Structure formats: C-alpha cells, structure tokens
Image (spheres, helix red, strand yellow):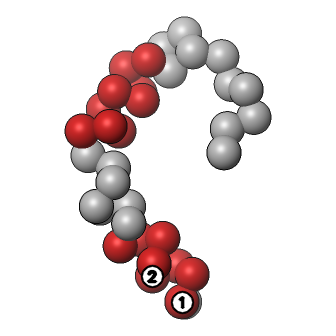
Amino acid sequence: AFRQALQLAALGLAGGSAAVLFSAVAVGKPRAGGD
C-alpha cells in the first residue's frame, strides 16, 4: 500500500478548503476528463 499511503497523506494535506469549492462549482461545471 505504498501508493495508497502517499496518495492518502497528500489527500488530508490537500483536500479541505479546495474540496468544498470543487463541489460547489461542480454543480454545473462540465466533466472534461478530470485528471
């Protein structure tokens, strides 16, 4: 779980204030592939 751990550490370190905004905009924001 080396990739599952690093991806999780950066998640809680980069998914709090920007997450609430991503969902607030996704209300109408089209899905252009993603990542």
Residue at 35 percent across and 38 percent down: it is: 19
In the displayed orientation, state which residue is furthest to the left: 17
Across and down, in percent, residue 29 comes to 57, 15
* Mark 1: secondary structure: helix
In the displayed orientation, state which residue is furthest to the top: 28
According to the picture, the residue beneath numbered tag 1 turns out to be: 2
Which amino acid lies under the numbered mark 1 shown in the image of this protein? Phe
Across and down, in percent, residue 27 comes to 48, 14
Residue at 34 percent across and 27 percent down: it is: 21
Across and down, in percent, residue 20 comes to 30, 32
Q: Nearer the viewer, residue 27 or 33?
A: 33
Residue at 28 percent across and 61 percent down: it is: 13
User: How crowded is the residue under tag 2: few (<14 C-alpha within 10 Å), some, or many (20+)?
Assistant: few
The answer to the question of whether label 2 and label 1 lie on touching residues, with beta carbons closer than 8 A, is yes
Horizontal side of residue 28 vs 6, given as left or right: right
Q: Quadrant of the C terminus?
A: top right
Image quadrant in which you'd find residue 32: top right
Q: What distance separates the C-alpha of mark 2 from that of mark 1? A: 5 Å
Residue 18 vertical placement versus 26 (above, below): below
User: How crowded is the residue under tag 1: few (<14 C-alpha within 10 Å), some, or many (20+)?
Assistant: few
Which amino acid lies under the numbered mark 2 shown in the image of this protein? Ala
* Mark 2: secondary structure: helix
**Residue 5's disc number:** 2
Residue 14 vertical placement versus 34 (above, below): below
